[PDB]
Amino acid sequence: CVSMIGGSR
Amino acid sequence: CVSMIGGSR
Amino acid sequence: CVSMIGGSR
Amino acid sequence: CVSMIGGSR
Amino acid sequence: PFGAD
Amino acid sequence: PFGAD
Amino acid sequence: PFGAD
Amino acid sequence: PFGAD
Amino acid sequence: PFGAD
Amino acid sequence: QQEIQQRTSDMLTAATQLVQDWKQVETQVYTEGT
Amino acid sequence: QQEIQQRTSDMLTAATQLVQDWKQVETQVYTEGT
Amino acid sequence: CTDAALAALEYHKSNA
Amino acid sequence: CTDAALAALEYHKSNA
Amino acid sequence: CTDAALAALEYHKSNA
Amino acid sequence: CTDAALAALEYHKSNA
Amino acid sequence: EVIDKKAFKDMTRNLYPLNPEQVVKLKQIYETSEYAKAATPGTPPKPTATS
Amino acid sequence: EVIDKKAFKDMTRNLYPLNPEQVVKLKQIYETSEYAKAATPGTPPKPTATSQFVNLSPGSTPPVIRLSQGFVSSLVFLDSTGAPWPIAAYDLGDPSSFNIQWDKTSNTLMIQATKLYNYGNLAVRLRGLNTPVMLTLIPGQKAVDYRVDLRVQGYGPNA
Amino acid sequence: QFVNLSPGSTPPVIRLSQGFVSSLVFLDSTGAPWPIAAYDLGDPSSFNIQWDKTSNTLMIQATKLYNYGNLAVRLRGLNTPVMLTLIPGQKAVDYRVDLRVQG
Amino acid sequence: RVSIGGTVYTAKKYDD
Amino acid sequence: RVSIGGTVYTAKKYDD
Amino acid sequence: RVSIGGTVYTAKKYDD
Amino acid sequence: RVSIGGTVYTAKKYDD
Amino acid sequence: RIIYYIQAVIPGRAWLIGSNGSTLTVREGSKIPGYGMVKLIDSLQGRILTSSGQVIKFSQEDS
Amino acid sequence: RIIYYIQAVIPGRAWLIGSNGSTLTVREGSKIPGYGMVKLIDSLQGRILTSSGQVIKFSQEDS
Amino acid sequence: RIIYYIQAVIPGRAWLIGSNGSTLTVREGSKIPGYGMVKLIDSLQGRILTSSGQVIKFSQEDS
C-alpha cells in the first residue's frame, strides 16, 4: 500500500 | 427471428 | 457486471 | 550513512 | 445489451 | 483505484 | 529516504 | 580527504 | 423475406 | 480542436494492439509419460 | 513553455524502456542430477 | 430488456 | 468505497 | 521519517 | 577530520 | 518541481491513454462484436439422430 | 563552485528523470492497465465437473459440452457399468474453432475452444459400438464442462 | 487439499505468482506419491510447466501474472484425470500444494 | 433488432 | 464504471 | 507517495 | 557529502 | 412437477436438462411439458420465457 | 456456522474455502449457506459483501 | 514474552524470526502474537511499527 522509496519528510 | 445482441432498451 | 478496476471514488 | 570520502574539511 | 445481465 | 486495498 | 537509516 | 591520514 | 419466419 | 483527432489516432493505435493481444489463442501441449 | 514537453519526451524514453523491463519473464531451467 | 424484445417480436410477426 | 461500486451496480441494474 | 509515512497512510485510507 | 563527519552525521539524523 | 507533475500527468495519459476503464470497455465491445459474428441466423437446426 | 551543484541537480533531473516515486506510480499504472486487459468481461464461466448418460436411441438429442476459449475440457467415456471405453477414432467437424488432443490408446479426448462462441459437433467412434457418439460442442457458456463423464448406452470391453 | 473427483465437485485452485514456482505434488488417500501418467497445460504461453519424465511433481511458473487458466494431468492408475485450475497473482502464492487424490 | 430476411423492424422505447 | 451491455453506467460521487 | 490504486496520496510535512 | 537516500546534508566548517 | 435448467443456450436453440436427467433442445416456438409454449430465448441472461409465466434459468449450482 | 475464506478472487468467480474443507466458487448472485446471497465481489481488495452484512476476506494466516 | 526479529524485509512482506526458532512473514495488516497488529513496515530502515508501540528491527547479531 505504502511504497516508502517514494519518500519525502 | 430476433438477434437480441442487436437489442436496445 | 461491475468491473472494480473500472472504479472511481 | 556517512560517505566520508565525499567529505570536506 | 440488457439491464438484467 | 480503491482506498480499502 | 529518511534520516533514521 | 582528512589531515590525519 | 416474410414475417412468419 | 486538433486534440480530439490526435487522441483518437493514438488510442486507436493502442487499441489495435490490445485487440490483437486478445485474438491470440495459444494451443495446448500434450506431454506423455515414461 | 517548451520545458514541459522536452521533459515529457525524456521520461517517455525512460518509461517505455522500463515497461519493457517489467514485461520480461525470464524462464526457469530444470537441472537434473546424476 | 425483455419488454423491448417482446414488442419487437410482436412488431415483426405483425408486419410481414 | 464500495458505496460507489454498489451505486453503479444498481444504476446499471435499473437502466436496461 | 515514518511520521510522514503514516500521515500519508491515513490520508490514503481516508480518501479512497 | 572526524569532527566534521560527526557534525554532518548528526545533521543527517536530525533532518529526516 | 511542478513541471515534473504536469509532465507525468501528460505521461500516464499518453503511454497508457487507455485508462483502466476504456480498456475493459474496449474488451467488452470486442467480444460483443465477435458474438454478433458468432450468432447464427435465427434458430439453428435442431440436432436430431433419426433412423 | 556552485555551478557544480546546479549541474548535479540537473543531472539527477535528466539521467534519472523518473525519481523513485514516479517509478512506482508508473509500475502501478502498468500493473492496473494489465489487470484491465487481463480482466475477463462479465461472468467467467463456473468450473463444473459433470456426468451424463448418453442415449443412442433415435430421437435422443446428442449430449452437449459447454466450453470456454483457451480452456481444456476432458471428455471421459464409460459404459453402462462405469468402466472405461477406449476410443477407436474421431472426426471433428470444424477443427478451426476447436483443437483436440488425444493419446491414441486412452479413453479421454480433450478439447479447447480456439474461438469464443463458434460451436460445432464431434463424432467419436468408440471400440465396441457400430454406432459412434455425436456430441455438440458449444463454447462461451456461463460454465465450463471442465470434465464430463459420458455414460454410454452400451457395454464396453471392460465389465 | 483434498481432491474430490465426484461429479458436482469444484476443481482445486492453485494460487500462482509471476515468475514464481508452484510445485504440485500428487499423493493418494494414504498419502503415498502417485506418479504422473501425462499432462496437458491450458494457456501454455501464460504458464510454463516443468516435470522430470517420471516423478509426481509438476512445477509451474506464471509467465502471465494475472491471465488465469486450467490444467489437465492424468495420473498412473486413474482413468479419470486430475483437474486443476491455476490462477496467478493472488494475495497468496502456493509454493507447494499437497494434492490428496481420492484414489 | 433485425430479422433473417434482411428487413429491419425495431421497437420504439421499452425499459425493464 | 462500464457494464457488459456495452453502455457505460457510472455512479456520481461516493467515498468511504 | 503514490498508492496501488494509482491515485497520488501524499503527506504535507512531517519530520522526525 | 550526500547520504544514500539522495538528499544532501553536509557540515558547514569543521577542523581537526 | 419436473424442473429443468439450461445446460446451454445460444441465439435460437437452447439445450435444457431436467431433474430426471432428460435433455431437450428448443427454439422460439417449441412445446415444453408443464411450462407450455416458449416465448423467448435470452442467451446472454441465461433466461427462457415460456407462456405459463415461468422463467427458466441456468442451474444455481451450474451458473 | 461455518466460516468461509476466499482462496482466489478474480473479476467474476470467487473461490472460497469453508471451515470444513469444502471448496466452492461463487458469483455476483449466488446462495451461500449461512451467509446468505452474494451482493458484491471486489477482487482488487479481495472482499466479498453478502446480504447478511458479513464480509468475506482472505484468511489471516493465508494473506 | 517472545522477542521477534527481522530476518528480511521488502516493501510489503517482512520475514521475521522469533526467539523459539519460529519463522513468519507479515503484511501491512497482520496479527503478531503479543506485539499486537502491525501498523507499518519500513523496509528501507528494516523497521516494523506495531500497535503495542513495540518496534521490530534486525537482530543485533543479525545486523
Image (cartoon, coloured by chain):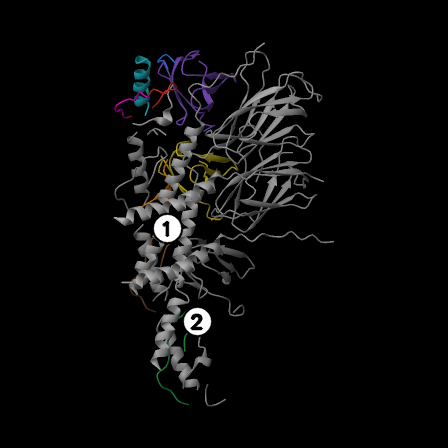
Chain colours: C orange, I blue, L cyan, S red, U brown, V green, W purple, X yellow
Left or right of X2 on screen, residue X53 = left
Camera-side residue of P34 and U5: P34
Tell me, yes or no, if residue X9 can be seen here.
Answer: no
In which quarter of the view is residue V2 placed? Answer: bottom left
Asked if residue P40 is among those painted magenta in the image, a careful observer would answer no
Label 2 neighbourhood size at 10 Å, few (<14), some (14-19), many (20+)?
Answer: few
Residue P32 position (above or below residue X47): above
Q: Which residue is mark 2?
A: V4
Asked if residue S10 is among those painted magenta in the image, a careful observer would answer yes
Give a yes or no on whether discs 2 and 1 share a subunit: no
In which quarter of the view is residue U10 placed? Answer: bottom left
Question: Residue at (41%, 29%) from the top-left corner?
Answer: P36
Camera-side residue of X4 and V16: V16
Tell me, yes or no, if residue L15 can be seen here.
Answer: yes
User: Where does residue P48 sit, x and y in percent of width and height?
Assistant: 53, 14
Q: Which amino acid type is marked by label 2?
A: Ile
Label 1 neighbourhood size at 10 Å, few (<14), some (14-19), many (20+)?
Answer: many
Chain identifier of the residue bearing label 1 in the image: U
Question: Residue at (43%, 20%) from the top-left corner?
Answer: W12
Label 2 secondary element: loop
Label 1 secondary element: loop
Q: Which mark is residue I2?
A: none
Q: Which residue is mark 1?
A: U5
Chain identifier of the residue bearing label 2 in the image: V
Camera-side residue of X12 and X57: X12
Quadrant where the image shows the N terminus of chain W? top left
Label 2 and label 1: CA atoms lie apart by 28 Å
Q: Which amino acid type is marked by label 1?
A: Gly
Which residue range is magenta in the image?
Answer: S8-15
In which quarter of the view is residue I5 placed? Answer: top left
User: Where does residue W51 sit, x and y in percent of width and height?
Assistant: 36, 13
